[PDB]
Amino acid sequence: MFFIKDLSLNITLHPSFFGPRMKQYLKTKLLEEVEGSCTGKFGYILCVLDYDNIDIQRGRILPTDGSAEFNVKYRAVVFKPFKGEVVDGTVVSCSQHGFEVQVGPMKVFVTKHLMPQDLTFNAGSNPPSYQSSEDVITIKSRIRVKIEGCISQVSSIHAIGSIKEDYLGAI
Amino acid sequence: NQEDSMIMNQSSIDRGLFRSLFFRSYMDQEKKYGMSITETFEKPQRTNTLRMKHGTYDKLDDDGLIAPGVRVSGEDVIIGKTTPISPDEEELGQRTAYHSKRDASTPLRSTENGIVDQVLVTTNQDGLKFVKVRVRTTKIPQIGDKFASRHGQKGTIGITYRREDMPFTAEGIVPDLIINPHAIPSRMTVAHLIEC
Amino acid sequence: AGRAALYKEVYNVIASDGSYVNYRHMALLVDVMTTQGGLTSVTRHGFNRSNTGALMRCSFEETVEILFEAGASAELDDCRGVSENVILGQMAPIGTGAFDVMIDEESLVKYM
Amino acid sequence: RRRRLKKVEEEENAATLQLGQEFQLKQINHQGEEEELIALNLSEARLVIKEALVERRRAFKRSETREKELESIDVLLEQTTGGNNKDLKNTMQYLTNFSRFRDQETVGAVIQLLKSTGLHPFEVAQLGSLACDTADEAKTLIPSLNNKISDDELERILKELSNLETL
Amino acid sequence: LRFGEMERDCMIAHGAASFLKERLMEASDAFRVHICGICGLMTVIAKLNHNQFECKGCDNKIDIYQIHIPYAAKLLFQELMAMNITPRLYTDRSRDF
Amino acid sequence: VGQQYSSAPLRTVKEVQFGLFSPEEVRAISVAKIRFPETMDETQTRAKIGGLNDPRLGSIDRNLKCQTCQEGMNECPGHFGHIDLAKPVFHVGFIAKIKKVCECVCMHCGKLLLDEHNELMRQALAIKDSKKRFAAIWTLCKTKMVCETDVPSEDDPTQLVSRGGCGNTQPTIRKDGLKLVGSWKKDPELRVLSTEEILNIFKHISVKDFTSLGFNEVFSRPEWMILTCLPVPPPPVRPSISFNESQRGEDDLTFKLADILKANISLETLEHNGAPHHAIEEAESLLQFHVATYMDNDIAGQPQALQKSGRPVKSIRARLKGKEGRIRGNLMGKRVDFSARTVISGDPNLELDQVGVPKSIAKTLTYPEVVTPYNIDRLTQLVRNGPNEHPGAKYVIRDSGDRIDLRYSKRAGDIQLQYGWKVERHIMDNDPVLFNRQPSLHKMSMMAHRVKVIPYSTFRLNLSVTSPYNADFDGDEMNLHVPQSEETRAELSQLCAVPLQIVSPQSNKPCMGIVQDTLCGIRKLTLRDTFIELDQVLNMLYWVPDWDGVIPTPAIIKPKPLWSGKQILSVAIPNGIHLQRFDEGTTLLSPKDNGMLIIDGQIIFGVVEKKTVGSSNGGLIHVVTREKGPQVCAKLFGNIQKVVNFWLLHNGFSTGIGDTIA
Amino acid sequence: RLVKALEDIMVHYDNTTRNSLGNVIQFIYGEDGMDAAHIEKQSLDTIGGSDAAFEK
Amino acid sequence: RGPNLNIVLTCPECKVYPPKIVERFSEGDVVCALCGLVLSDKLVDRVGEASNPLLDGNNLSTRIGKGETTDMRFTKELNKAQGKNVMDKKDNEVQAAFAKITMLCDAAELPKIVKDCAKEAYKLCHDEKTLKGKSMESIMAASI
Amino acid sequence: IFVYQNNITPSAMKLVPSIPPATIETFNEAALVVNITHHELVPKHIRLSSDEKRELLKRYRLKESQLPRIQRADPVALYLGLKRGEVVKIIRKSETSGRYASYRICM
Amino acid sequence: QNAQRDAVTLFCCLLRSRLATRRVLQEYRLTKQAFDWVLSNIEAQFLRSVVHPGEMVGVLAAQSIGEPATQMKVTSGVPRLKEILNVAKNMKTPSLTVY
Amino acid sequence: CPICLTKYTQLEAVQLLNFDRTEFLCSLCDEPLVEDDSGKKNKEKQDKLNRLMDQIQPIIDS
Amino acid sequence: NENFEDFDVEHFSDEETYEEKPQFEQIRRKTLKEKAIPKDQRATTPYMTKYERARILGTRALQISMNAPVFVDLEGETDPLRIAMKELAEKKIPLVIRRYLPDGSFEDWSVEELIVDL
Ligand SMILES: [Mg+2]
Ligand SMILES: [Zn+2]
Ligand SMILES: [Zn+2]
Ligand SMILES: [Zn+2]
Ligand SMILES: [Zn+2]
Ligand SMILES: [Zn+2]
């Protein structure tokens, strides 16, 4: 979920960008690979705050490839999920293995062993969705899902969702 | 020629001064590791032989041995030997069912060249056929080749001059070789002078 | 006084054949050999026993035993010596490596 | 300092307030002092990101219903953000589709409401995120609220959040 | 060609640190290996195509650094691991100078 | 092709921490449990799962990926396995340390024999470093034969405080091969101490107890000294070599792990199926011996494990220590690429800082040059020249790391170069190269020269530079090294160059000087009898490269224009140089023409000799390199060598048998 | 043996002479801080001669 | 069945299968013969002992011998410890049979190829149901 | 200061450690016939005060162990009666700079 | 500052011996610009003569000592050097020099 | 994965999901994964637990 | 192989001889800003050393070889090292030098302010 953090990033500035105006180049090259970037250390970083002043240290010239190495300390909003967290979202894809719900920039999977037994798969219906005796869960449908387990790699985060808990599912 | 170098007459080198032959013999043997794990002196073909060397195979014959008299160059194969491998493998991409054999041939040295002097085929004590190929080349003396007198005054050739550049007597005799005076007093080699 | 006599002996050995060496070299030798308060010999049991890094010590002599003692004692190597950077293949903090090159921005933007 | 190896620690969880080693309640900023961990609800995060994007737009330039705001933030991300902004875009559509407060006044009212509760910023941000209507629903949705808040005060918070919720 | 002890000594006497590093790495064996952050060992499973790093036994997927060492140094450290010795490599100082 | 890009941060190793694996750590880091002593499958074509060459450990065939990291040779570092030992065994490198710790600690309750209730123990605790403190503790506690369950008070030896300890009798411990025997005292009871007992005792040792002994609590506990989970090194540690690409000869290490698995399986079957006790000690002694000779084959008082050929098994310690060991043979110094080696020859026509590189060597050694606008045309021309013509290029490295051989690519057409690409072009002239003569006792014996590509097979070099190399052209090899980066090229040119190291820091005097024929000819040239005619004078003047183009006025105008040898030699000496030296019997008039006087780079009197242009302090070389700089001194070396060698060529100098005759 | 004894000793930026551990060997290098290559043998005029020559 | 674990050396630019590949052993490179792009660099062309796993199988055994400083009591102790091993009993008797076969060949000066053929003939036909009751002298004689 | 003649019983050595700050030094008459300080090889040793030692460590940015050492058994150290952690300024004649001032800490 | 004063006192002695008023005004006969040139050059060469920080003087000293060993009553030479470096309690010719 | 015979938990099945958002492709075998038969034996484990414990009650009483 | 009476010393070979004779804080702490000595009280030499000039030339030539913006007028010079020496000649190299003291502290000296006398 949504946090704000003070992060320090190490950036390889190439010697080709040693122009008179490296500050906006450094801020820009911060701003491609952070916006929407996923890190397992802090979650999905979305937007960088305090763009007018960002702490830029005196850069390290690496002794082999000549590139400048800057430890830029910045403040940004992040999306770090956890397990045990219930969130709202919309289903973007479904299958017999389960369905993917979109919570922010994240596609949380709900596995086929994690719905209540009333829901069942019907591939004959277009789009193929999960149908129960009391509700139906299709593509682009509102649903409330709880996350029971999240795995975070160095650059990717995957989560496990369910709707077996009471007061979950479609609102 | 300073400090253990010589200046050798290049015209003398042209006329055969210190020119010499160099024979190298290559011995290769086919052996049976068991029933069918053996190898055969044969000229390999690209259709059915795996892991050949990049040197040319054209100088070989039907028996996988180069005839004597044929000039050889660097990394040319002189003894073509192949052994079968386990069929229907998958290695390096260029592996098919045709490649029933791998190449165990013997190339020449990467720097050596010359003429195949004599090819000798026979059997060993064990009755296995093995070959000996003698390659003859000539080492014309050049810059850097080491020469010694009979007095411990060794050294390399510094440079080679033609006859018109070397000093000469009133009789027109040029030296074949110039040594330096500085080789004499430190070593106290008087017998070199007395021998001269 | 032992250091002075040691320098005198080393100088006598060097100048025995008339060969001349600048004073600071043998001065550095006898200062290293007497820096611990004792005549620390240049042996596998002399300078090779000070806690100067496991990799530096194992590079000289008794390599496997030194690594055994380091593993038993859980010795931490600060990697400031030359030999540790040789084995790690990184820039030794010597000569050109004895500093770091930072990039300036203020004079750079002052240039034009 | 820290004599580091694999020591004993508990796995990350929501009900135990274990948000990891680096999400502590105390946080060290870039200036070095301790500062409270700040977690934002969906509407608060949407407004904060919107102010950040329009501030970036103003910095670049110096050198309501759901549909029109949606296309406004879409063209704002098109003109402000560069490459690989797909995740940020979908985050913006998620934030607009699941927001409960539209203006900064309602968000500030929620913040001043939840600052005096004495609970964690994490759980009050979860409370502002979720449109709960029952105290037992709030207890079974956010397990950290168990034995933390009284049920009548909890119901007051949910009913006043529902009153403050618009559109 | 052997760039042995005494050639290294003369390069040290010149102060030519980066040339010595080049000879020892870019001229013989520059091997890039990944190490865990928790343990200093090189027991990191690296799926570079999948961009997935993890040191199983420390169960961390976010604390992995890559280093450039000689291949002989990696084989040294693996042999010391076979000696039941830990060549724990750390990318930061823990003790003050 | 290089290596695949990695998203992990690239850092440098700042600290190396030592210690011992815990067996739990061994089982944690292990990717497989090795069970079968076989390496190969029963079909003799694939890797046996659970064997010593399990694919999860790694892969040492090019056409085989590692099963764990899914990489080849150049990326997989190899992954460790483990052996679950049937019984604990001793680390053979720690037998003395285990014995010392056992003499320090109780054999029943696992407590220190002497606690802080003794003054000697407390002052032993005052020692800061681990080794000296442990030695003092061991020397103090090796003489204690009882656990001392009750001790007198430290402040007053009148009342008895009951400290920890069971009061039992600690036996004397000695090693007899690979096992420890303990002799209890007789009120001697001697028996062999089992390794599991020692492991239990070491587990019962508290944290502070071995902390006082110098053992760190998470990195090296004394209980971890006993091996009970042996880690399996990956096949990159123990590769399977091939003799003719048909044999499967394995490493000695793999042989030893096969023996380890055989002994371990034998021991667990013997304990599982029931056995007499002596069979159990026999099997565990065999296992311990196999562990030891795996870890150290050279044990004093012990037999050595032998190969099928009968040679001793190369243990890991043998691969570590020694000349061809890992450290001194592969790490602390090593074989390198971009090097060349051939015989050397003198060249009076080369500059002092210049080396003559053979054309084939120059066609072989390459320098990767980065493509800029400043060299796009030159590098494109070198690419079009190809690798078979000097100057040319052998490889083109694209910005993605892809390397294009210039052979096997012209038939694909020419290549358009892009900025930031690398071109591995042949070394042209003036390339800074390291030039080294082994044994290389000192820093002047390996220095940086400039390339001059020459059409023969010898490293050619100036005569004056042979003295610091201690080089003679009687067949000496002498090495070459080419830097591949601009940083190292620059620091080689600016730190290791020949002119910068004219003056030796060894003895604060020049290490290079005018030698041999040039020295003899410069003595013969500066005699007072030596006068040079116009025709030879003009040639001598033109031989100086930096001659200003003005003919000096002759020393003798009439009846014939004659220049003295000093007059022509002073042209090589740059202006502003003032050298003054007085020998014995030397005045301002020199009847012997001894000593020297140079004024404004003009020789006044005195024959030029070893005391002047030799490697001597206060000579011409020292003065010029201190007042004019190193480049001017190198040019002086070249000028003097050229002019003196030319004059000696047209003068001649010999020696004969008559010269030794009185 | 000597090189391995002295392989880690460097003149630092405070002009001290320390090993890898930072232990000071010489507080100033060569007791004078002068590079060895920039040293020449020179005669000290005051120490030699007589007192009359000193005054003259 | 089983993982692939196979690396194919295909040019990612020429895209011709199967590719013409030249192995520059001297230059340490593996290149595409068409475009000249390298595929695998730093190629590998002594330290162990020769052992063909066809004549004696995958037996990996080292015996115990006297070193520079060797005590004899541990030597006999380790020799008898190796003597009572159970898993190599069939291995022990097949090497005993190989030793007797080689002794028979050497006692009648037969060439080494006959020794190899007899040893592999015995190994391929050891432990047969149809060949169990015949005398080991006859087995060796038939193999010879 | 205790000056004996030939030898001491070890039963007195065990009680040479006394109540601090009172300190006992046992000096042999035979070892004290000639002042070793007057020897030409022995340089001038000057004991440093605590503030001097602190300033020396501060200006050279040193730790305690990074100084050159002298043991607490050196004849000059016994002559000055040095204790542990005491630094002496050692001034000796330099053939390159006339006067060289070294420092040694008593261990 | 005390260490800097002590480090140059021999060179200061040499400078005062050479650049005395009697010697300058009698032997050297320098002018104003000549004397200023002399002082500037002496200062410049002295600052150029300072040892550069970062220099491995340990390896330089070790090489400068070990190399003249290769160039080679009381014992002397390589065995004496070995007796010195390997600090042995015994030696070939233990001796005194009593004055 | 039946080809590589390697187990996978629920957490890493999501990162093996394909572009079709239906199947879980193996990393090494590139083959869709099959479901392990664990979890339906939970009642079997409960029956095993009870059938062990009614046979141990005299030991409990002793 | 070969049989040579030409006595070539195989090198790095002293372990024959080893086997012959085998028997015989308070100003600065942690990572604070106190390591960064301020410019007013820097105690290192203002003269840029030979190693410093070598590494500046190497770094600048490496950067110029990868299209760094050259801050001096080129005179037709194309070699990166001579361009770097020209940049150093009129102090146009935008680098500063971090001279580490032995205690871990450091001083920052710009190439512009360092005196290049050698
Ligand atoms: Mg020679
Ligand atoms: Zn780890
Ligand atoms: Zn692998
Ligand atoms: Zn006890
Ligand atoms: Zn291609
Ligand atoms: Zn699979």
Image (cartoon, helix red, strand yellow):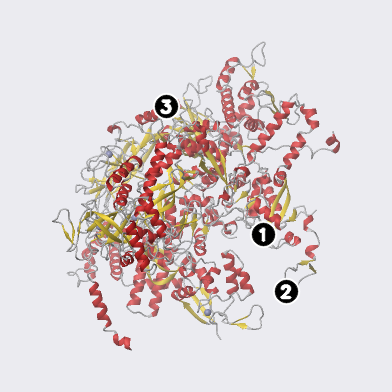
Q: Is residue I106 left or right of residue L30?
A: right
Q: How much space separates mark 3 and mark 1, taking CA atoms?
A: 67 Å
Residue sitting at x 62%, y 75%: F118
Say what secondary structure mark 1 lies in.
Answer: loop
Q: Residue furthest top?
A: F559
Res F354 visible = no
Q: Amino acid at mark 2?
A: Leu
Q: Same chain, marks 1 and 2? A: no
Q: Same chain, marks 3 and 1? A: no
Chain under numbered label 1: J
State the residue position of label 1. Answer: J90
Chain under numbered label 2: I
Q: Amino acid at mark 3?
A: Arg
Q: Position of residue F644 (x, y in %)?
A: 59, 25
State the residue position of label 2. Answer: I15
Q: Same chain, marks 2 and 3? A: no
Q: Is residue F600 above or below residue G13?
A: above
Chain under numbered label 3: B
State the residue position of label 3. Answer: B15
Q: How much space separates mark 2 and mark 3, taking CA atoms?
A: 99 Å
Residue H81: image quadrant is bottom left
Mark 2, Cα crowd under 10 Å, few <14 / some 14-19 / many 20+, is few
Q: Where on the image, by quarter, is ligand 5? A: top left
Q: Position of residue J58 (x, y in %)?
A: 60, 48
2 and 3 marks in contact (CB < 8 Å) = no
Say what secondary structure mark 3 lies in.
Answer: loop
Q: Amino acid at mark 1?
A: Asn
Residue sitting at x 62%, y 25%: F574
Q: Nearer the viewer, mark 1 or mark 2?
A: 2
